[PDB]
Amino acid sequence: SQSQGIQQLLQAEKRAAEKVADARKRKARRLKQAKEEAQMEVEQYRREREQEFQSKQ
Amino acid sequence: EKKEKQIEQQKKIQMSNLMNQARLKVLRARDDLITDLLNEAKQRLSKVVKDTTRYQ
């Protein structure tokens, strides 16, 4: 059963490797999402400031 | 700020034109007062020449 205990541990290692690689992929995804959301926020900010400007004029 | 306040500066520009023209308006009114006085003086001299001995 030595070979099997080893294989089971290797499977655990494999999963660990997968879990962090997938986390890094998510990180990349989250960063792109951050940029798009940021721009969307910028657009809302812009609309508000546009309104303030027109109000002031 | 540059541009909405640029419009604000145009309004300041607007205030400059209003104040400068207002100054001319009151100055012109004062010049009419002088002109009207001179015209009245001419009428009073007309009254003088209507005399005989004083005009002679």
Image (cartoon, coloured by chain):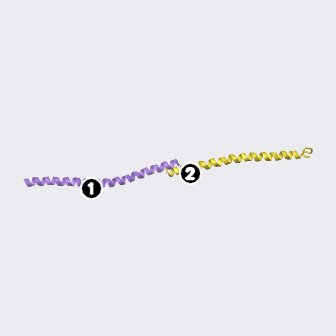
Res. A25 mark: 1
Using the image as rendered, state which of residue A20 and residue B12 is in the foreground: B12
In this image, A22 relative to B8: left or right?
left
Residue at the (69%, 47%) spot, across then down = B27
In this image, B41 relative to B27: left or right?
right
Q: Amino acid at mark 1?
A: Lys
Secondary structure beneath dot 1 equals helix
* Colour that chain A carries in the picture: purple
Residue A33 in the image, given as x and y percentages of width and height: 33, 54
Res. B10 mark: 2
- Label 1 marks a residue whose chain is A
In this image, B48 relative to A18: left or right?
right
Instruction: Same chain for labels 1 and 2? Say yes or no.
Output: no
Secondary structure beneath dot 2 equals helix
Residue at the (83%, 46%) spot, across then down = B43
Q: Badge 1, how many Cα within 10 Å: few under 14, some, many 20+?
A: few
Closer to the camera: disc 1 or disc 2?
2
Q: Amino acid at mark 2?
A: Gln
- Label 2 marks a residue whose chain is B
Res. B45 mark: none
Residue A13 in the image, given as x and y percentages of width and height: 17, 53
Q: How many marks?
A: 2
Q: Residue furthest top?
A: B54
Residue at the (17%, 55%) spot, across then down = A14
Residue B19 in the image, given as x and y percentages of width and height: 63, 47
Residue at the (75%, 46%) spot, across then down = B34
Q: Are marks 1 and 2 in contact (CB under 8 Å)?
A: no
Chain assigned yellow: B
Residue A29 in the image, given as x and y percentages of width and height: 30, 55
**CA distance for labels 1 and 2:** 53 Å
Q: Residue furthest left?
A: A1
Q: Badge 2, how many Cα within 10 Å: few under 14, some, many 20+?
A: few
